Image (cartoon, coloured by chain):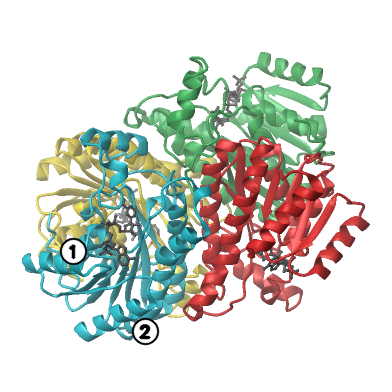
Chain colours: A yellow, B green, C red, D cyan
Amino acid sequence: MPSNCRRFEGKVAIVTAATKGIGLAIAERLLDEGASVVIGSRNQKNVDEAIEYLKNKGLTKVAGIAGHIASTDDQKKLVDFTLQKFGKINILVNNHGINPAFGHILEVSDQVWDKLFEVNVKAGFQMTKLVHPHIAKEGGGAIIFNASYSAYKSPPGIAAYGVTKTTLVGLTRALAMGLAKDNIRVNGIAPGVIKTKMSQVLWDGGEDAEKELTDIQEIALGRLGVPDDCAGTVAYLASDDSSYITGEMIIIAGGVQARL
Amino acid sequence: MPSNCRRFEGKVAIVTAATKGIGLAIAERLLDEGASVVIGSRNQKNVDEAIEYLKNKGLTKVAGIAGHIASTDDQKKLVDFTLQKFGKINILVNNHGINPAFGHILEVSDQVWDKLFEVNVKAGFQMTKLVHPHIAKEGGGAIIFNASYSAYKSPPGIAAYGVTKTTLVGLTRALAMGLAKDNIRVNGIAPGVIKTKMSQVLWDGGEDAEKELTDIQEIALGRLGVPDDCAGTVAYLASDDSSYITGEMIIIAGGVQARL
Amino acid sequence: MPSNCRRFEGKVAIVTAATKGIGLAIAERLLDEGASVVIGSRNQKNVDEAIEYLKNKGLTKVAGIAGHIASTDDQKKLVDFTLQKFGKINILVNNHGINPAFGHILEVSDQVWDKLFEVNVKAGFQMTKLVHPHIAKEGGGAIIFNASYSAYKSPPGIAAYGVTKTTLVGLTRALAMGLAKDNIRVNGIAPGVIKTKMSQVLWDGGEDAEKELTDIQEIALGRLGVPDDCAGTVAYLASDDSSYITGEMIIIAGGVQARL
Amino acid sequence: MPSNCRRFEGKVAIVTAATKGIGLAIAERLLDEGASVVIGSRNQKNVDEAIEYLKNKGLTKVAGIAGHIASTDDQKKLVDFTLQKFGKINILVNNHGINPAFGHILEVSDQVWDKLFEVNVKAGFQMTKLVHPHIAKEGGGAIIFNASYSAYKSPPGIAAYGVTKTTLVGLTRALAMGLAKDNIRVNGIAPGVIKTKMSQVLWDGGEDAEKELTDIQEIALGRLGVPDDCAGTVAYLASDDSSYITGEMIIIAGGVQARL
Ligand SMILES: NC(=O)c1ccc[n+]([C@@H]2O[C@H](COP(=O)([O-])OP(=O)(O)OC[C@H]3O[C@@H](n4cnc5c(N)ncnc54)[C@H](OP(=O)(O)O)[C@@H]3O)[C@@H](O)[C@H]2O)c1
Ligand SMILES: NC(=O)c1ccc[n+]([C@@H]2O[C@H](COP(=O)([O-])OP(=O)(O)OC[C@H]3O[C@@H](n4cnc5c(N)ncnc54)[C@H](OP(=O)(O)O)[C@@H]3O)[C@@H](O)[C@H]2O)c1
Ligand SMILES: NC(=O)c1ccc[n+]([C@@H]2O[C@H](COP(=O)([O-])OP(=O)(O)OC[C@H]3O[C@@H](n4cnc5c(N)ncnc54)[C@H](OP(=O)(O)O)[C@@H]3O)[C@@H](O)[C@H]2O)c1
Ligand SMILES: NC(=O)c1ccc[n+]([C@@H]2O[C@H](COP(=O)([O-])OP(=O)(O)OC[C@H]3O[C@@H](n4cnc5c(N)ncnc54)[C@H](OP(=O)(O)O)[C@@H]3O)[C@@H](O)[C@H]2O)c1
C-alpha cells in the first residue's frame, strides 16, 4: 500500500464529503504523499472521528469543518477555512454526491430531480468557481470529480442519480477546456460498486450476496471495490504524473464495460 | 426530398419547440409520412405562421398551442390539447432547448445554470412523465431527444449549455432502460452546427464566414447543416425502421469526431 | 411494416455476403425501395436460392455472383459484374464477416487471427478501394459496414472476432474522413445478437434459452434481433435521410449499453 | 518531478521498442521505481546507447536485446532473455508501433495495410500470449498497450495507422476480459502528439509551428507532449495504484476531445 510517492509536498487540497468512504481514503493518500488537506462533511462528529483517525496514523497536516456541501454559505466557509488554515489551495476533489431515491425513474419527483442535480452537480460547479482564483494564483493545480460508472451504464433503481453522474462527465470536460488557460487540469473518476455506507444495501447479505452482485454487475476482476481502490487514481490525477491529461474520466470498476 | 415513406399513418406526435428550425422540419416530415402532429412554442404568432406554412403545403393533420415548455401548467396544457385534438399520443419529440449565455463557464451564474438545466433537461423529463401513460396505452411508441454534438465535444462560449446536452445523453439512456418495459423506445439526435435562428451569430457574415466555421468545426463534409438534415433521422428513430434500437444518440454533424 | 419508402430508385448497391441473414434482408429492403442490387456469397447454390427468393417476391432488379469476399480475384469480379449488369455503383454494403473460432482469446492461433482480420476488415478496405472511383463518379454515395455490438462490449468466446469489429469502427471513421471529399458517406451498424445461422450456438435452446440470453445480455427490449431489424438502418444510412451523417456507428442491440 | 514513487521493487517488466522516445521514458520510470526492466529494439547500437544512458543515471537493473518485435523468433528470444536475466515477468508494456505510410488511406497498399496490423496489433497479441503464463505464475501483473489518441480521432495522412490503434483499444479490452481470471490487468494509453522521431514531421518547423499545431489539434493545455508525459501513466497502470482498473484507455493528449 505505501507507495513512497510524495508528489504532494507543499500542496493544499480540499476533499469534499471526506469523512467516510472514498473521500476519506483520498484524503489519507494525499496526506501520505505530503499534502495538507481540508476535509468536510455535514456532521461534526464524523469530522471529529475522521480527523482523529488520520492523526492517529501520524497524518497531522489535516483540518476539518462541518458543512452542507450544497449550502452556499458552507461552501464559502469551507474555502475560507482552507485559506485560513493553510494559506492557499492547489487541489479540489469534489467527492460529494448523494443518492436518496430508489425506484423507477418515472417515480422521481421534480423536486427530487432538482435536489439530485443541486448536490451532485451544481455544488461541484460552485466549489470550482470558489477555488478557481486561489488555484490559479498558485500557477495551476487540479480539480477532480468523483462521478460514477453509472454515468456510462444507466443502472436500475438509481437512474436519476446516474444521469447526474453523466452530467459530471460533461462538467469535468467543460471545466477542463475552460480552466486549461490557468493550467488547472480537471479530471474525474467513475467508480463501480465500492463497499461504503452508500452502496451497503447492495452487498451486506454475506459473502455470496457480494459474489452474486459481482455477478450481475459482470465485474471481470470478480470482486467489489473498496475506498482505497479510488485513491491511487485521484493521487495520480492530481499530481504531475498526469500533467498532460485533462478532461478525462477513469472508470474504476474492476473491468465493467461501458465505453471504448 | 420526398421519400414516399409513410411510416406514421395513424400515429400522433408531439414535437416541442417546433415552430421554427429543426423542430418545424421534424414536424413537417412526420406530417409527410402520415402522422397527426401537435406543435408548440412560446409565441402564438410563431404557432400561427407555422400552422399556416404546413397547411399551405397540404399538411393539415397539425395543430398548435402556445406555451412555455418549462411551465408545468403549459406542459399539461400541451399534452391535454394533444389528447383533445387527436385522441392519443404515440410519439414525443423533445426538441426544445435554449442557449441564453455566451461567455466563459466560470461566468455562468448559479441562476443561469439552473435555468439551463430547467429548460434543457428537466422539461424533457417532465414531458416524458406526462406523455408516458398515454404512449404506453397505445402499446408503445417513441420518445426522441434533441441533444447536441456539443454533448460530446465541449464548445467554447456555450459550455454550460453543452453540459446540459451531455445530461440529455444520460437522460435518453436512462429513459430508454426504464421505458423498455412499455415498449417505448427512447433515442436522441446530437446535431452539429445547423443554420437556424439559434446558431445565426456563428454563420451570418456571408459565404466564407460559413466556410471559416466549417473550418474550425472540422466538418468532414465541408458545409453547415440545415434543419431538414435532422428530420430524416427523427423519422427513422420514431418509426419501426428502428424497432430494435433504444438508448442511442445519433450525431448529425457532417463528420465531426467526438466519440467512437 | 413494409414502409412504402422508395429512396433508392435509380441507385445501384452491392451488398456483400448477402445470400442469408442480415445481408439478404439488407438487399431485400434496398430492392423494395427501388434499387438495383448485386449480391454475392461463396456458394453458387446460396446465390441461386437468394435470387429466386427475391424474384419470387417480384424484386427483379437483382443479380448475383458467387465468390470469396477476401479473394482479390473475386472482389474484382464482383465489382466488374456489378458494372456490367447495372452500369454504375452508388452504394456498397460491406456486410461480410466470419467467426470461425470459439474459445479463449489466448487459444487463437496467429493464423486464425490473421484470417479474422483478412476477411472481417481487410476485405472491406479492399472492396472500398475498388468501388471508390465508381461511386465518386456518380457524385457520391454511401458505404456501410456491418460491425457488431461486440466492437464495444468484448464478448466471451469470440473476443478475437470482437476485436475485428472494433477495428471496423475505426475503419468506418477513417474512410468517412477520407472519402468526404468525394461526398461518399461511410457509416456502420453494430448489431447485437441477431438470430441467424452465425449466432445460432448462442440462442438455440428453445424460447426461454432466448429469454435467458436476453437477461444475461441485458437487452432492454427483452428479445433477440432478427435480420430485418438491421435493414431499416442500412437503408436509412445509405439514403438521403442521412445526408449529413458520416463516420457514425448505430448500435442495433435492443438497448444493450456499451458506450455513451 | 522525480516522484520518489517506488512501486515496482522486485518486479520485472518488459518494455518493447524502448530504446528511444516514449518506450525509453517508460523503462526509465519503471527503473526509478525499482523494477528490473528488459528493453528491446531492432538496432543493437540503439540498445547499447539506451542501456548506457540508463546505467549512467545509476539505473542498473536493466538489460537489452536487439530484435524485430514482429518476428516470432525475436519475440521468443525477448521473453526467454528476460526469464534468463531476471527469472520472471510481472509486467509487459507493448509500446511498439510503426507508421511507414503518409498519404491518403486509399493509397495504402494491401501489403502496407497488413504490415501495419502485423506490427501494431498482432505483435502485441503474440507478446501477450508468450508472457501470459509467466505473469500468471507470479499471481498476476499487468500489460499495457500504447495505442494513440488517433484511435479515437481519425487523423489525416496516417489514417490506416489510426485504425490499427483503434484495434488496440479493442485488443486491450478483450485481453482485459480474458486475463482477469489470472489477475492480469490490461490497460492502455492513447497519447496525443508526443515529440519523438516518429511524430517529427508533424511538429518540426520551429516553436510556433508547434504553437500552430496546438491550435489545429485543439490541445487545451497549449503544448505538445514529451515522452515523459506518458511514463507516469504507465507506471500508474502497472502498479497497485490501479489494482481495480482493467480494460481502460487513458488519453494523454493535453485535453484533445475524442470521446466521452
Ligand atoms: N459507494 C459506491 O458504490 C460509489 C460508486 C460510484 C460513485 N460513488 C460516489 O462516491 C462519492 C462518495 O460516496 P461514498 O460511497 O464514499 O459514500 P459514503 O462512504 O456513504 O460517504 C459519504 C460522505 O459524504 C458526506 N456527505 C453526505 N452528504 C453530504 C452533504 N450534503 N454535504 C457534505 N458532505 C456530505 C458524509 O458525511 P456526513 O454524513 O457527515 O455529511 C460522508 O463523509 C459520491 O459522489 C458517490 O456518488 C460511490
Ligand atoms: N441550431 C443548432 O446549431 C443546434 C445544434 C444542436 C442542437 N440544437 C438544438 O435544437 C433545438 C432547437 O433549436 P433550433 O436551432 O431549431 O432553434 P430555433 O430555430 O431558434 O428554434 C427555436 C424554437 O423553440 C421555440 N422556443 C424557444 N424557447 C421556448 C420555450 N421556452 N418553450 C417553448 N418553445 C420555445 C421557438 O419558438 P418561440 O420563440 O415561439 O418560443 C422556436 O419554435 C434545441 O434543443 C437546440 O439546443 C440546435
Ligand atoms: N448474427 C449476429 O448475431 C451478428 C451480430 C453482430 C454482427 N453480425 C454480422 O452480420 C454479418 C452477417 O452475418 P449473419 O449473422 O447475417 O450471418 P449468416 O446469416 O450466417 O450469413 C452469412 C452470409 O455470409 C456469406 N459468406 C460467409 N462467408 C463468406 C465469404 N468468405 N465470402 C463471401 N460470402 C460469405 C454466407 O454465404 P456462403 O456460405 O454462400 O458464403 C451468407 O450469405 C457479419 O458481418 C457478422 O459479423 C452478426
Ligand atoms: N510520437 C507520437 O506522437 C505518438 C503518439 C501516439 C502514440 N505513439 C506511439 O508511441 C509508441 C512509440 O513511438 P515513439 O513516438 O516513442 O517513437 P520513437 O521515439 O521514434 O521510437 C520508436 C522505438 O521503436 C523501436 N522500433 C521501431 N520499430 C521497431 C520494430 N519493428 N521492432 C522493435 N522495435 C522497433 C525503435 O528502435 P529501433 O529503430 O532500434 O528499432 C525505437 O526505440 C508507438 O506505438 C507509437 O505509435 C506515438
Q: Is residue A158 left or right of residue D60?
A: right
Residue at 49%, 45% in the rendered image:
A112
According to the image, label 1 marks what residue? D29
Secondary element type, mark 1: helix
The answer to whether B150 is drawn above or below residue C248 in the figure is: above
Separation of residues labelled 1 and 2 (CA atoms): 25 Å
**Chain for disc number 2:** D
Q: Quadrant of residue B43?
A: top right
Neighbour class for label 2 at 10 Å: few (<14), some, many (≥20)? few
Q: Is residue A62 visible?
A: yes
Q: Is residue D53 left or right of residue D86?
A: left
Where residue C1 appears, as percent x and y from the top left, is 83, 49
Secondary element type, mark 2: helix
**Chain for disc number 1:** D
According to the image, label 2 marks what residue? D133
Q: Is residue C129 left or right of residue D66?
A: right
